[PDB]
Length: 178
Ligand SMILES: Nc1nc2c(ncn2[C@@H]2O[C@H](COP(=O)(O)OP(=O)(O)O)[C@@H](O)[C@H]2O)c(=O)[nH]1
Ligand SMILES: [Mg+2]
Image (cartoon, rainbow, N blue to C red; front, side, top):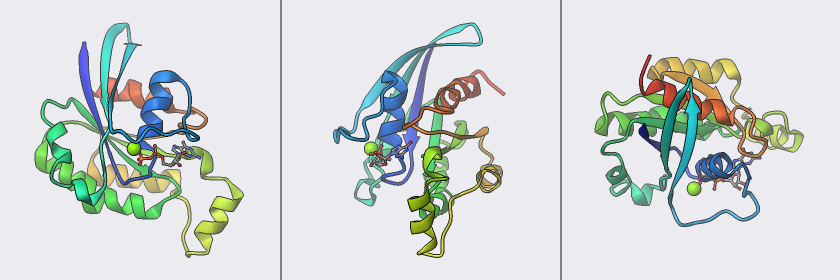
């Protein structure tokens, strides 16, 4: 089974790390590739063999017109936001969900909270407070998920890989089907 999955969301939520941490089981953080690319993984899910094509995106505003060229024939989207970036969570509803739905009205969405590992980091919570902000909590992401009617809400870390595999199994599970 060939499944095409597109990953959207604000620059720097960790889309490229998520894809590479997934396909290769190692985290770039140190050396992140800047050429926007597509990747591949052969996965077994509920006894069915799957070839999953993962398509990265340029979330920059400069790419508003060209980004949707990679949307045709997509089987499932991950809309991603950083659990340590409220601005990114805001943009799911202000920008990403509306753009996905504009081009692909019926394609399933998985809502993904990323950098799960920084949610307890001290220096991180601290910096967030200096802006009168705080990490997105599980209940908050679940609510956004319900707002936008995504098939699942899932948290992960590319750095630790916690929950990373489930993100992709549910992606696959959402195509073929509820
Ligand atoms: N601590 C932590 N940092 C991450 C994680 N995923 C990505 N990052 C960092 O976040 C920054 C942006 O990640 P990248 O994948 O380039 O984001 P993108 O622009 O959405 O594709 C980089 O500095 C990464 O090292 C994560 O799971 N944990
Ligand atoms: Mg990237």
